[PDB]
Image 1: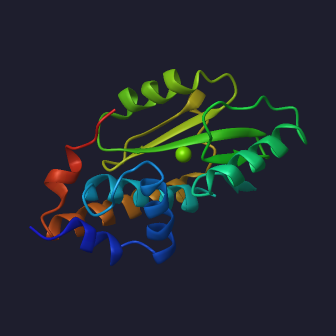
Image 2: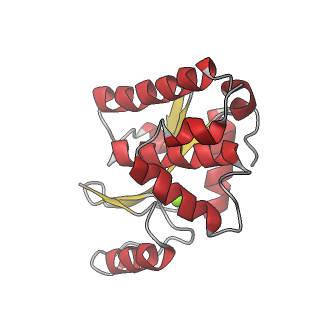
Length: 175
Ligand SMILES: [Mg+2]
C-alpha cells in the first residue's frame, strides 16, 4: 500500500495537480488528508482537458469561470447554467457537464441530471470500466477521441493498482 498523495503528484501533470489543490482547499478540504478525492479531482480535470472548439470552464477560479460563462450566455442566446459547467461547445452551442465515475454510470448520469435541472446542458459520463453515457446518445466526440479518454482512465487505474491504491479509491466515491 503506497501513498495516494505521492501517487498523484508523480502521476498527473503539475498543472492538473495544482488546479486540483485549489479546487480542494477552496472548500476547506485538505489534499493531504482526503487523498482519494484529490486523485478524483485530477482525473476529472484531466478528462476535461483531453475532451476539449471547446471552452474550458472547469479548473478556472470561480470568479473567472462565471465571467467566462456569463459572457458566453450573452454573445449567444444560451440560458445561464446554474452550477458551473465543465465545458462549452460552440459547435453544438451548448454547455457540457463531464463526469468520471467509479460507480454505475447510469446512476451517476441521473444524479448529475437531477442536480443541474438541465434543459440544454449536455451530460457525458465516463467510467474506469469503459462504459460511457451521453445525453440523447449524442456522444459529441468521434470514436478514436473517446477511446483515448478510456485508455487514460485504464492507465490511471492500473498504476493505482501496482501501488495498492485502487481498492480504496474505487469504493470511496460518494454522491
Ligand atoms: Mg465542474
